[PDB]
Amino acid sequence: DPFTQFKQTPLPYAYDALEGAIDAKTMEIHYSKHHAGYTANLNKAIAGTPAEKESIENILAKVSQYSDAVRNNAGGHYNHELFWSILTPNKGTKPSAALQKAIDETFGSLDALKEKINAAGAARFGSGWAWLIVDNGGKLQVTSTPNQDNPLMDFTKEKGTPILGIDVWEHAYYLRYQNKRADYLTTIWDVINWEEVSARYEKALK
Amino acid sequence: DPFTQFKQTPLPYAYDALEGAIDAKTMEIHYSKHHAGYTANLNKAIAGTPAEKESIENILAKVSQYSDAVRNNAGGHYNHELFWSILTPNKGTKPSAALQKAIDETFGSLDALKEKINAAGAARFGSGWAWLIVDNGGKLQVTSTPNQDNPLMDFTKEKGTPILGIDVWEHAYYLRYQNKRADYLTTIWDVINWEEVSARYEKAL
Ligand SMILES: [Mn+2]
Ligand SMILES: [Mn+2]
């Protein structure tokens, strides 16, 4: 149906393509149940409301004005859209020169960045997301948020444009890693698409 | 070590005893990793604070005076201690006469209560718990809380003494049910120990 406000973008890889880090059954459920549900519920939640014709970024920027259903499902849809795009089965991607320079000046190295994101992910009590954002000053920052909240929401303490997000809801890792979220976080770097993160960085700075 | 402030109560059944609703792997991890972690981190978080020799209920009742680590781990420890106690492998328990009468007068029937708890559990976005509590009015109430918060915590709006809690963190159900939290909630009734719920009701009154 071309007239629904929001649609899930198909994955640019197979469900089993990320098996170095994420099991195929999790990819399938995470995409076809969890994310699909957020998108469907988003469309329902904004229908007949002032949010109905707003872009996802604009919904999020005013999310405190809308229902919890809008907030939770707008977050969910946005976060997952971004998540799938920053994963890849193509090994050895790396940050663009511009991004790498910013990473090194801000964190020291790519390993130091990964350590900071891993720590943020591990410290998120309950469900949530770890983020690398470009803040409103153009500077990189690592944050985490609860549930499906994200750095574009007016509610959020550390605001910025996300360029990388890692889902630390238990559904994202429990089938393969159970309670070992840290092992999930260590391993997911194997499938991060730094080309997409770098594109998001370039667009954020504009 | 007998001197630790909080200990996990041994499980009163085997890890595979609840397979009518909860897989053995989940029980083992849930108990020996998630709950054990809360208990250990609680003991650490209270060390050298005014909470150090307080009862768990008294920590919860004043929880906002303490760190977030105390809140999260006191809630974690409390909630799981209660949770294990209200599960059983023995089919066919039922509320006491007193609890059954109260349930019927307040919700209509046991089925109506289960429906209300199932709905509360399903509606809890993210991690958390569904509860049946006794409010200070003696009245039964169904609520939910986020994360490891619970109805004994000082800041909680819907306060009361929990007599039944059902964990809806994904770790409680993902290995067996994956996204199907509603199926977990429907099925868990088969292992609820209404004799313990009823003993908790008696104590709460
Ligand atoms: Mn997710
Ligand atoms: Mn739990």
Image (cartoon, coloured by chain):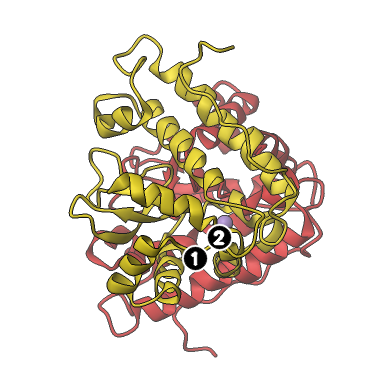
Chain colours: A red, B yellow
Report crowding for label 1: few under 14, some 14 to 19, many 20 or more residues within 10 A (C-alpha). Answer: many
Task: Check mark 2 vs ligand 1: CB closer than 8 Å? yes or no.
Answer: yes
The x and y percentages for residue B34 are 59, 36
Q: Is residue A22 above or below residue A41?
A: above
Q: Residue at x 43, y 79 (%)?
A: A43
Q: Is residue A33 above or below residue B201?
A: below
Q: Please identify the quadrant where the N terminus of chain B is shown.
A: top right
What residue lies at 37% left-to-right and 43% top-to-bottom? B149
Mark 1: secondary structure: helix
Query: Which amino acid, mark 2?
Result: His
Where is residue B102, by image quadrant?
bottom left
Q: Nearer the viewer, residue A78 or B50?
A: B50
In three-dimensional space, the C-alpha distance between marks 2 and 1, rounded to whole angstroms, equals 5 Å
Q: Secondary structure at mark 2?
A: helix
Q: Which residue is at 48% across, 34% downward?
A: B77
- The residue at 36%/15% (across/down) is B52
The dot on residue A21 is none
Residue carrying label 2? A80
User: Where residue A20 sits: x, y (%)?
Assistant: 81, 46
**Vertical arrangement, residue B53 with respect to residue A106, above or below:** above
Residue A80 lies left or right of residue B149; in this view the side is right
Side (left or right) of B162 relative to A28: left
On the question of residue B204 being in view, the answer is yes
Res B22 quadrant in image = bottom right
Lateral position of residue A80 relative to residue B152, left or right: right
> Which residue was labeled with disc 1?
A77
Residue B55: image quadrant is top left
Chain holding disc 1: A
Q: Badge 2 sits on which subunit?
A: A
